[PDB]
Image (cartoon, rainbow, N blue to C red; front, side):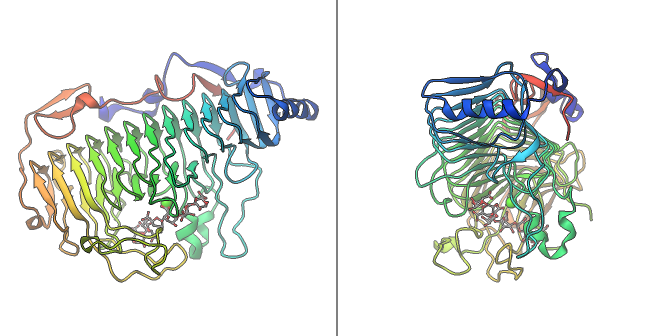
Length: 496
Ligand SMILES: O=C(O)[C@@H]1O[C@@H](O[C@H]2[C@H](O)[C@H](O)[C@H](O[C@H]3[C@H](O)[C@H](O)[C@H](O[C@H]4[C@H](O)[C@H](O)[C@H](O[C@H]5[C@H](O)[C@H](O)[C@H](O[C@H]6[C@H](O)[C@H](O)[C@H](O)O[C@H]6C(=O)O)O[C@H]5C(=O)O)O[C@H]4C(=O)O)O[C@H]3C(=O)O)O[C@H]2C(=O)O)[C@@H](O)[C@@H](O)[C@@H]1O
Ligand SMILES: [Ca+2]
């Protein structure tokens, strides 16, 4: 039952063999090289079956062969430590059952660089892989380096049934480095936990905070330069626990993506549609469990579909009129006049692709927000010129053509909570409301054509509130636990 869910419940499974660090022996400097040659000499169709044990500092491992599989002999029993990067240049390469821990990426784009087509990372575990690379404020502006753990640079990549635990230095955990055509990557059934910033005093450099406090997402799909092309990639059926990297939990920066059916539990970070068009966010379960700085989905740019999400028990910061509030659904302001067809454009100074595309043409329907401190927030935030230029942008615009239908914001338990935060500072343009139900405070409610303040009949189905005829259909929702997400083993005797 939802309120009573905890880390223990989501991560328990019987199906999970336990692998223990100690039954593994530390390979000598000599067997590492022997392992490395095996890697580098493999031919199309071959397979390496890493014998069990701990292998420190493989360094740079380049796989040039196609149709190969590198697996541990027993899943979870080959531990790759110190500095390593697998560089997967071949097509149809599969990594399976590996553990990356007690070490760090050998180059900043991660332990695994998936450069080929149809590359796969499955059944693998990353555990606090934060070590052994240089990590200092740089001389130029005191910026700490961005290190990722996995990056995808090819097509049809798969990252499935892994565990990604304790990323706690700067850098996005999975990055998609794409080009001008669809990538169709699948990132699914993974477990993500305990991403967290400022564990090494990074924020102590006050002047550098805006950038040092950025780039701690769990995944970024696309980036500013590539954002106006489709990725058509999927972030689905993942389980995320205490993922507190930064404001963006998932930063979508390309088009036609699906970010659907994830369970996001006690994670002080939001799904963020940051750049790019026509992304779909559906059937997620966002369970704040009353943790401060939790929230649902924040939205820039055009043509997105946000439907049938279940967002509960989220809470904003502890005690500014203009604050970028974390709500269940946040319709951001941006810096371009989209109501008159303005676009971001790499050629127009101040309006480059990495800036803020005022949301437009957004479908928001059949969501259930339950006990959310800030429910649906219509943004009034300002923006800075860039991460390196602190000047505020003059020229801020509200969302346009935002269609709300069949949403339930239920703050019946604490009706002082703000269910809808409308704002005369930036009235939405062309907003419409069809069968909305908002229970709880509505700020600037005279901005809203109509809505009901009485809940439909409420039932409980497998722990969820079901509102008759409205809100998220509970038939489409279910909690992801370690019964389908994550590797088939847990590791014991690991070190952070
Ligand atoms: O607390 C409050 O209430 C308010 O706080 C402040 O406002 C803050 C906001 O609340 C919110 O955080 C907001 O965040 C901004 C942010 O400042 C910035 O504009 C960012 O923009 C995205 C852009 O795309 C940007 O260029 C950058 O992306 C870079 C970056 O290097 C990133 O790591 C990534 O790198 C990869 C890329 O492939 C690259 O080419 C290179 O290869 O390396 C890759 C890698 O290392 O992974 O992509 C780059 C790029 O492609 O350009 O960051 C992006 C992102 O993080 O999404 O996000 C904005 C956002 O709204 O999310 O603004 C904060 C702020 O401090 O201004 C206060 O100002 C006030 O409003 C409130 O009090
Ligand atoms: Ca960010």
